[PDB]
Amino acid sequence: LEAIPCSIPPEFLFGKPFVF
Image 1: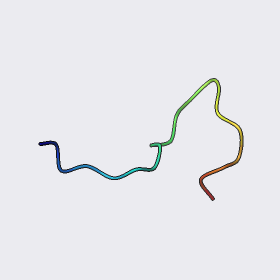
Image 2: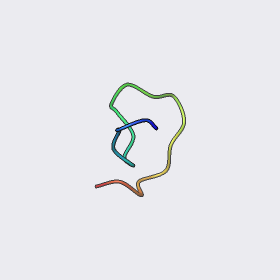
Image 3: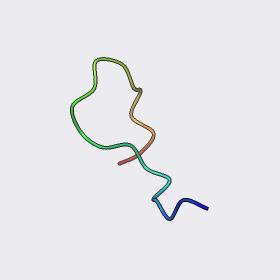
Image 4: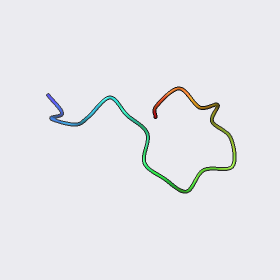
């Protein structure tokens, strides 16, 4: 069981604006 968020960290080549 991993205790982690469901959002992406900064510093990415690809990733549409769905986390702001």
